Image 1 (cartoon, rainbow, N blue to C red):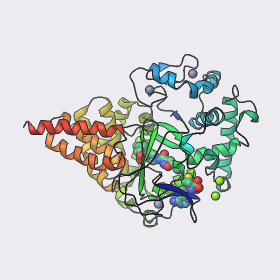
Image 2: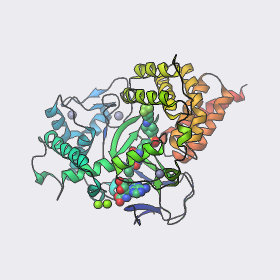
Image 3: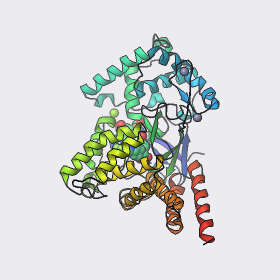
Image 4: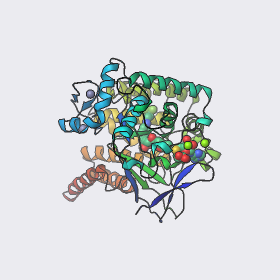
Length: 426
Ligand SMILES: O=C(NC1CCN(S(=O)(=O)C[C@H]2CC[C@H](NCCCC(F)(F)F)CC2)CC1)c1cc(C2CC2)on1
Ligand SMILES: Nc1ncnc2c1ncn2[C@@H]1O[C@H](CSCC[C@H](N)C(=O)O)[C@@H](O)[C@H]1O
Ligand SMILES: [Mg+2]
Ligand SMILES: [Mg+2]
Ligand SMILES: [Zn+2]
Ligand SMILES: [Zn+2]
Ligand SMILES: [Zn+2]
């Protein structure tokens, strides 16, 4: 018995609404992807199948592009990799855009696979394309993706009889652009891109009543507020650390809509997000383009070097509540954790705690993860009362956003028991 149902909204296309009253933390839907792939930066760093990082990965011998954590993952991935393998090998050394590799997997799944549970409420065929809202520049970009797909897939798909009935590649890429999900690992690093057509029914809010979280490729949809019968379910499509102007640009560019929510009408939190000297944070925002690229490719030493030059600059500095400063602290923290620089990681992480309380109101999985990271760093440094407070706060958030079905909650329970045993021996 589903707790959610598809419906036709008055002015947002189709949507999802509650069939029963919902409480924070309630699991509403869970889904594997219709199709997914590792993303550009994480290719060869994480396993193609389970999206977990490993010090050494085994490569597919035929294409040498797909890489796996284990013989189990390589073999289990073979049915969904078999046809793309010949295309990837034929295209070497050229690697396709993520969207092109993704749509290849969509096509093979729809041609060769049984009907997917991911499409229970809504299918790839049903997805919004927004084609009549596309500007000419966007249509041109989609045409180039179509031609890139035809080149990449030529070994496996030569004509329309090898595509699903009435399949239009331009329309398919339009759907991919507006309906791709960024798959994040347990630490909230972007590691993949996938299509989850039933989850695509969720419309956007900058102050949503639901949240999604990834456990490998698996997606969990949970309520994060009380929700009444008939009430529309929403998620936030975007990073919370964005001004209303930034959200406006991305929602127009990628999703072809103008957001009418209260936060956008009132520029909610914009002024607090942009405190400090504008010339300074404009420079930091510029530097973050490279920092974000380095982080996406797991280049932690390079990330840390650039972040330290900002955090410890000889020149003017920013308040930690400035969102570009905050992003630099976040990246520096994550780099230090991955490099084993645990004292420095804790310094940066502790500084983010109050800004995160302000910018992630309610129960948000990203703040849950951040607080867990800080609590774990404090546990390792022997600060048991401080660690316990943060681990308990992380649990209060993550019991709602992640839940028992997410493996990170089991990890958190072990940290809480270890911290508690230390306190009791003191
Ligand atoms: O992919 C979808 N949403 C995303 C929203 C964002 N999250 S997140 O949980 O906040 C994790 C993010 C936290 C920030 C992190 N970036 C930090 C970079 C900072 C810099 F630049 F300084 F380096 C990246 C991960 C993931 C899911 C989606 C699609 C749809 C379709 C339209 C239906 O809905 N939702
Ligand atoms: N808050 C919002 N206001 C207006 N349109 C929205 C919206 N959130 C999502 N959408 C629409 O939904 C698309 C994302 S997919 C969400 C389901 C979609 N409404 C459908 O009918 O299939 C966006 O590109 C936009 O067309
Ligand atoms: Mg349509
Ligand atoms: Mg329309
Ligand atoms: Zn694996
Ligand atoms: Zn291969
Ligand atoms: Zn809004």
